[PDB]
Every structure is written in C-alpha cells, then in structure tokens.
Image (cartoon, helix red, strand yellow):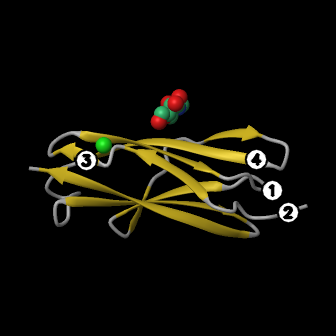
Amino acid sequence: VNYPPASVELFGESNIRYGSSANIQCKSLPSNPASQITWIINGRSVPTPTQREFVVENGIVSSSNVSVHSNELSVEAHQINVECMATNPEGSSAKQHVIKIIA
Ligand SMILES: *[C@@H]1O[C@H](CO)[C@@H](O)[C@H](O)[C@H]1NC(C)=O
Ligand SMILES: [Cl-]
C-alpha cells in the first residue's frame, strides 16, 4: 500500500553556453504517499520553489521544473552536476544529470 518512488525521471539540456540556463525537469516515479522533490547542485541542496503532483493508478507522481543558471559560482570543472531526489516516508530515490558548459 505504501512504497517509495522507484526512481525519478530527469530531463534537460546536457550542453549549454556559459551565462545561460538549462531547463531541467524532474518527475518522480509513482509513490504512496506523495514524494517531496529535492534538488542538489554540485553536492549541496538548493530550494524546491514548486512541485506539482499528479495521481496515477499506483500512487502519486511529483514533478518539478527548475532553471539552472551557469555562472562562476555554479560551474565546477566546466560542468554543473544536478541531482534530483524524491523522498516519502518509505524511502528515497535519485538520479543525476550533468550539464556540460561548452566553450
Ligand atoms: C516542465 O517542463 C516540461 C518540459 O521539460 C514541460 O513539458 C512541462 O509543461 C513543464 N511544466 C511546467 C509547470 O512548466
Ligand atoms: Cl543538449
């Protein structure tokens, strides 16, 4: 009856020009109860401004869209490591997405 999200779906630009932002979307796989989306940029948590929840047959999908801005403090070794985590009381799952900053 209750179970954690089995994984997350992570979509977005994989290469962007320095100074621009990448549109990143995270969608949890279905969970019960609903999961909270947390974002991690280069190893540190950042706010989740909004998340949107949908019901499916199994449980609930949580979705969050963010824009990741590339600048001198967010870029490390010419990339940005983005991780999305989906957590409910039964456990959590996560995926990472690497944004390359092109020269
Ligand atoms: C989130 O982004 C996806 C494309 O990556 C888009 O289809 C969807 O409508 C967006 N949702 C919101 C609330 O912006
Ligand atoms: Cl791309």
The disc, 4 or 1, on the residue closer to the chain's N-terminal end is 1
The quarter of the displayed image where residue 41 is located: bottom left
- In the rendered image, residue 61, in percent from the top left (x then y), is placed at 70, 46
Q: CA distance from mark 4 to mark 1?
A: 6 Å
Question: Which residue: 58% across, 42% down?
Answer: 51
- In the rendered image, residue 40, in percent from the top left (x then y), is placed at 42, 62
The type of residue carrying mark 1 is Asn
The type of residue carrying mark 2 is Asn
Residue 60, labelled with which disc? 4
Residue wearing tag 2: 2
| Label 1 environment density (alpha carbons within 10 Å; few <14, some 14–19, many ≥20) | some
Residue wearing tag 3: 15
Q: Are marks 4 and 2 in contact (CB under 8 Å)?
A: no
* Total numbered labels: 4
Q: CA distance from mark 3 to mark 4?
A: 31 Å
Q: Quadrant of the N terminus?
A: bottom right
Q: Are marks 1 and 2 in contact (CB under 8 Å)?
A: yes
The quarter of the displayed image where residue 75 is located: bottom left
The type of residue carrying mark 4 is Ile
Residue 32, labelled with which disc? 1
